[PDB]
Image (cartoon, coloured by chain):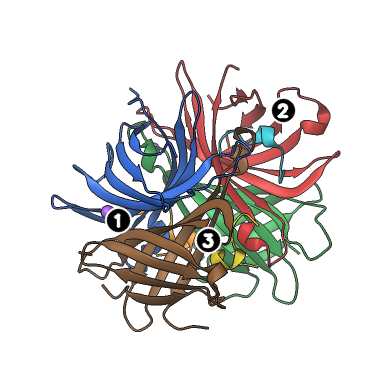
Chain colours: A orange, B cyan, C yellow, D red, E green, F blue, G brown
Amino acid sequence: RDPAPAWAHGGG
Amino acid sequence: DPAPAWAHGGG
Amino acid sequence: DPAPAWAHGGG
Amino acid sequence: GITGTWYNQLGSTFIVTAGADGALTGTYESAVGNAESRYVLTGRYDSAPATDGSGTALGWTVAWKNNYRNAHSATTWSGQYVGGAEARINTQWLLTSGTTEANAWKSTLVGHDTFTKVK
Amino acid sequence: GITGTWYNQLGSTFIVTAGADGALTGTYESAVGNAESRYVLTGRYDSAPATDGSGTALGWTVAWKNNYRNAHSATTWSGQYVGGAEARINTQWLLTSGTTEANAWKSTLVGHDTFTKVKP
Amino acid sequence: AGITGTWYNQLGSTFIVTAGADGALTGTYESAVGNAESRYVLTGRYDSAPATDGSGTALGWTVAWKNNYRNAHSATTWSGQYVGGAEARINTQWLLTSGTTEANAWKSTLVGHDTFTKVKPS
Amino acid sequence: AGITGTWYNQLGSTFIVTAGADGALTGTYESAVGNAESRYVLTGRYDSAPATDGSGTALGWTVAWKNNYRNAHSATTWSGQYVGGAEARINTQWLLTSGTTEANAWKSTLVGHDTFTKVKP
Ligand code: NA
Ligand code: NA
């Protein structure tokens, strides 16, 4: 689980 | 200052 | 500079 | 609960409308409140937050240009609103200056601030 | 320079307009391109920057709620636009989740990202 | 230097620190929050010859969150300054990084601010 | 642990560290030139028993910017993780705090990031 979309933060 | 000091309470 | 720039990836 | 006026400990005055679309819009100014000290802000907030006492996530930006001054910099505040009798907006901020590439390492200050509904 | 479509290295797609008044508006979405991954952004930029080679200061916010999903969180990006042959936006970000008071100490993540107009 | 002592942050964590003549910080940290129990080793550095113009004393320290009771696979650094006078205080910002996979690295680092005083606040 | 030795950022700024069985990081940080006036003491901590699930090794360190030649009245902390394998790296975020008066404390702390590798550029 993530606290926000990972793609948006340069990750995931 | 790089911006108004009043606008930035804690460092 | 507040510290050596080279140490922080800059300058 | 967000719409209205908020103050930091110095009495700097944050005037915001929280729209039904999730928008934050308003102005930020000094305790004196002269026009030269007033800047536009815009941001976003969670318009359907938890109902359990948790804070409401939000953020906003001020670019430090108005019709009188320009510092070539911008601050973003990231934080949460907590309501009730002693409502608060608790934030951390990043202040980035426009710099040359050689000075970019020292372009961004970090800090914090807390806003309340009374001075 | 700022107005356009920007990408991070994962292909996350930042479609922004820089208005005459200092406004940033637009959307941010995943490389998959689906509506459920698209979010509103708003921010501000210096509309009269220095012209000596310095970058243009700017910031924006996304709250992680759209018509489909809500993470109960918001990210702000603070940074500068660097013009030239390969224009770039370099940012630091803060991601705050709504929390109880007891968990507020661990509410905020920090990181960095860089954007260009070149689709990866 | 004024730094050696037992300090408490706003969450009730306990910071037991010694400042050495050479700029060393040593001691133990006990966190009131997070994946932590009992004491952890800390080390760091401080300015052993601060400015004489009223400025605070710059310092920083690290705790890796491993001891014999648990290992959170994480480390926190506090960066700040000591301010002497009537109500002595250490004001800090901190970064808590967890060991992660590359895919989760984006969410590896929490940030906050702690203020330490000699009083343990409610 | 894979940490002991010399690490370089993109400018070739150079730290030489020992990562002990005690969880200690001890060493020096200096410029690419490496003259004595550029060298500062580094002290920190790392996770000496990291997870075995493909996660990095958490660590952090501090440099106070005082040596025998200069004193900037400031200190930087780096918080990050060591990532082993074919191209080992230490990825960090940092906080640089200056000693300030109370009036200037709001602008005391810079934030940034840096990545270190074993290969001098
Ligand atoms: Na929530
Ligand atoms: Na430790």
Q: Chain of mark 1?
A: F
Label 1 Cα neighbours within 10 Å, binned few <14 / some 14-19 / many ≥20: many
Chain of the residue where label 3 is placed in the rendered structure:
G
Q: Secondary structure at mark 1?
A: strand
Q: Which residue is mark 1?
A: F74
Q: State ligand 1's quadrant.
A: top left
Residue E61 picture location, percent across and down: 58, 47
Compared across the picture, whether D36 is left or right of G61 comes to right
Q: Is residue D47 left or right of residue F96?
A: right
- Image: E4 above or below F26: below
What's the CA distance linking mark 1 and mark 3?
A: 33 Å
Callout 3 touching callout 2 (CB < 8 Å): no
For image coordinates 13% across by 49% down, the residue present is F69
| Residue under label 2 | D30
Q: Are marks 1 and 3 on the same chain?
A: no
Above/below status of D35 relative to D100: above
Residue at the image position 60 percent from the left and 39 percent from the top: G106
Labels 1 and 3 touching (C-beta < 8 A): no
Of the two numbered discs 1 and 3 in the rendering, the one whose residue sits closer to the viewer? 3
Q: Is residue E1 visible?
A: yes
Instruction: Say which chain tag 2 marks.
Output: D
Say which residue label 3 marks: G68
Across and down, in percent, residue E50 comes to 82, 57
Q: Nearer the viewer, mark 3 or mark 2?
A: 3
Coordinates of residue G14 in the picture (x, y in percent): 48, 74
